[PDB]
Length: 197
Length: 197
Ligand SMILES: CC(=O)SCCNC(=O)CCNC(=O)[C@H](O)C(C)(C)COP(=O)(O)OP(=O)(O)OC[C@H]1O[C@@H](n2cnc3c(N)ncnc32)[C@H](O)[C@@H]1OP(=O)(O)O
Ligand SMILES: CC(=O)SCCNC(=O)CCNC(=O)[C@H](O)C(C)(C)COP(=O)(O)OP(=O)(O)OC[C@H]1O[C@@H](n2cnc3c(N)ncnc32)[C@H](O)[C@@H]1OP(=O)(O)O
Image (cartoon, rainbow over all chains, first blue to last red; front, top):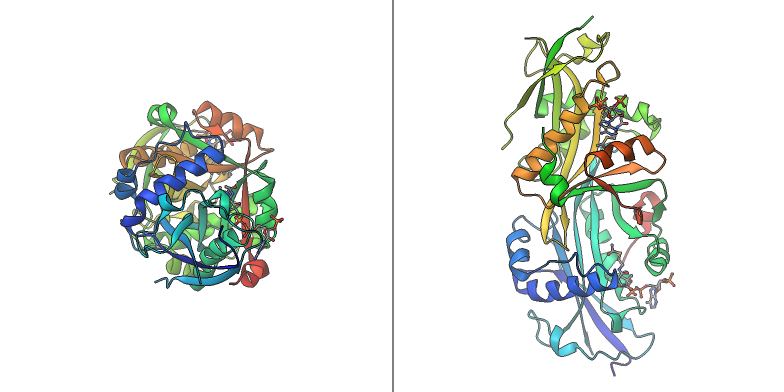
């Protein structure tokens, strides 16, 4: 239904975006088949995000489309194939009514001990199913990398499930290196509460 | 030379710890045999650390020993073996002249979108050779975990080398889980410089 060219906008999320973000987090949990592990609510986003200045704590960028600290990034995209979005009314942008929310990225600063320099870690990057494969995920990730470089970051890092070959190829298509020697350790739930001096 | 019991103190690093932190980071890089990729200087530490409130950005806790917000953790430690430290004079603590700096831990907040809660990520944790194998590294790790639970962190995370099976065993014994499917991706150097919109 959406044909030709679209105008993509990447912009800083505000508290008004909390419901769209909760919806996109839920969709992302389904994609990773971890919907049971996802307990996100809008109140939890209000309690944990927008506490610190952007790029100084957990920060979210929204990706929205329409047709024709961080300033919004606006780029035109020629659609690879027409877009059939049967959920556009549920993703209407709260900022500009005539935009459709199709994605988000959540990231926060990290630190390299050997560089003695801060960087950025991308925790989540998601684009709604009808909008994948036409350059939108690239714009969104490139927007974070762009601001990170403006803030003199040494590295930009993120994780990847080794079976998400679609994301692997996408990430390596941007010059990133998938490191094979590192494993994440997580202490949480009962074990975290039981861990004591 | 050092026998019986020592008093171990874990405290927040201040900018006065930068010379010891840089020495300890060089020792850590030397241990992991990545000293050429290690460009840490005290000036870099002064430019990247102690800029945000502790536990709100990259934070270092110092571990020191003697023989008799974050409040210091002071614990008595029974020495499993006599300790001979010839680097003692080079690691005299600023906080107290009679204390010896034996280690450090660097960590920063992270964020879980599935929990919609901030957590903590431990980037590096090091203890000097003469003081290993007597419980000090465990006190350092549990000191970060204890503060993370007090700040109601959802998770506490770190990375491990996949071949370091002894570390996987110890972390598993603590209740931590080594995730099998996650890989770290890194965008740095010329690829980071070329990544543009
Ligand atoms: C921990 C995490 O969050 S991992 C993040 C990944 N998330 C997921 O896997 C969830 C579901 N997937 C998605 O949301 C998305 O598909 C993403 C985020 C992986 C990528 O977003 P997309 O919009 O699909 O990517 P985009 O279209 O920009 O680029 C992907 C491919 O298109 C190519 N491409 C780049 N620019 C364009 C363009 N203008 N037009 C068409 N294709 C393009 C890239 O070279 C890349 O090629 P490859 O995958 O064949 O190697
Ligand atoms: C959490 C992290 O990021 S640790 C990863 C970096 N660790 C390194 O390998 C750097 C060099 N090693 C060291 O500085 C230390 O030996 C540390 C930091 C691993 C802690 O060791 P200790 O002070 O000896 O631990 P402690 O005496 O409390 O525990 C007994 C044993 O438990 C294990 N253990 C304790 N803490 C750790 C840890 N953080 N990682 C892996 N194994 C550990 C070790 O096998 C240790 O014996 P070791 O000193 O002979 O290696």
